[PDB]
Amino acid sequence: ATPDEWRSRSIYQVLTDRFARGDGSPDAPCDTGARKYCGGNYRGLISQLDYIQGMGFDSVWISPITKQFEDDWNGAPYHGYWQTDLYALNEHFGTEEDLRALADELHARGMFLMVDVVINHNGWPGDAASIDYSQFNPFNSSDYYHPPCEINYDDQTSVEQCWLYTGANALPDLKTEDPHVSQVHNDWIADLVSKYSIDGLRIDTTKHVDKPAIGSFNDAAGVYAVGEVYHGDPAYTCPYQDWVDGVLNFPVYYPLIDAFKSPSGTMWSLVDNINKVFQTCNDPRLLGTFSENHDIPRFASYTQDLALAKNVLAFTILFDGIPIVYAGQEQQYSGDSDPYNREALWLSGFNTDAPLYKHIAACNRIRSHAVSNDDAYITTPTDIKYSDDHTLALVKGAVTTVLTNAGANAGETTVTVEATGYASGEQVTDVLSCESIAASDGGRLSVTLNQGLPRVFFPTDALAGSGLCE
Ligand SMILES: *[C@@H]1O[C@H](CO)[C@@H](O)[C@H](O)[C@H]1NC(C)=O
Ligand SMILES: OC[C@H]1O[C@H](O)[C@H](O)[C@@H](O)[C@@H]1O
Ligand SMILES: [Ca+2]
Image (cartoon, rainbow, N blue to C red):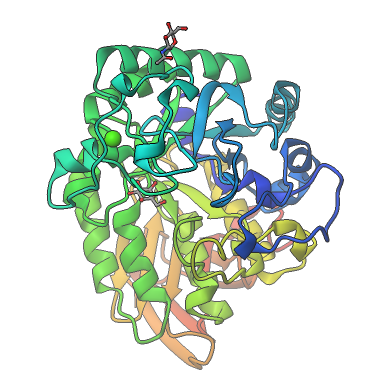
């Protein structure tokens, strides 16, 4: 699927091993500290797609699928980022039949499959010096790899040419810029995308790969790719969108978490980074918006406050870009680091009564109803119509999203949002509370916030067929 087809999508990210098991158990243990395979698989994922669709997600980004190393003495490669063979599958997740059945079933539901891919490196269960290169496939010689060194983070060519790690487990760094390696990577992905009907990619460790290699890889794939560019500065991350269709929105992530992790936070750095991303990135609406992933602390590890989590999720889903929710976020999983942030989802019992499950469902539903209602909604830029220390109002076509970090104990506050684009007198509904008000002079909206809850407005007349608020 093209970048254009990906615009209205929203993504539920899973660690395959940690989402759902084929045998349907919601009680197989997953001691996150053990770093073993817990047993999640493709047939498990297929079995719980109603859970995923129930939240309004229409795409799934799964762990890398390639064969890993076998020796688990220093941890099992349950996360898929330690590959040895591009041409074979990790059979812990399933056979090619299982994976083909995943793609088929996603597609029967009108969903998209996004695959995580690593071209930066293979994995080895031992240090750099111990690596037997002949064991890798297809890059079965030291000739295809940069010499081992640790990265000097003040040097971009070191970021690209040194290794992510040289101790056990080592991450031998491929010569992605070598013509033969690039050729093989490109033929590989062109083939893999056809073979398994992949709709999009998520490219691991994109900043550690030279940009031209990224470009020809994305071209060869022939589908939308979002690059994981792990950097908070729009001046660094945004120029990557000249080479990949999208990047994950790390520049917005950092001030977002700073804003909403505590009522002590302020909106100003979020506003500033949003502006900067809009000034720097070719297309902010092809970026992946997230507030969690497997590398960073869970949101609920910063704060237990439900209203704060509702505000970050509202932003995550309703802001410009393609929303991404990390499996567990909706159950308020709280692991503060790797491996604790890879909790098994099945252990929550796939609880559709969780408040953040229902919250995500409503946010996704109004976003998708907005896409349905107006062809131009998805490509219309979000404007910041109001900001102060503790409040942000985002207007994207006819959707007005009003957020606050005042938290659950806030009491009551009133904010007046000027120039929303609603007509004076136009009745709008906050689809989260099903409470209804009207716009006033010049599109002015008088918004009262209570107990730190976000509000999401949509014109009341246009709400029919939504499933929202009767
Ligand atoms: C890698 O594979 C090729 C093709 O079989 C073979 O000729 C070559 O000897 C291998 N290289 C090493 C270092 O084993
Ligand atoms: O897992 C942590 C890693 O996330 C990524 O894949 C980043 O690109 C890399 O810089 C970082 O080490
Ligand atoms: Ca590299």
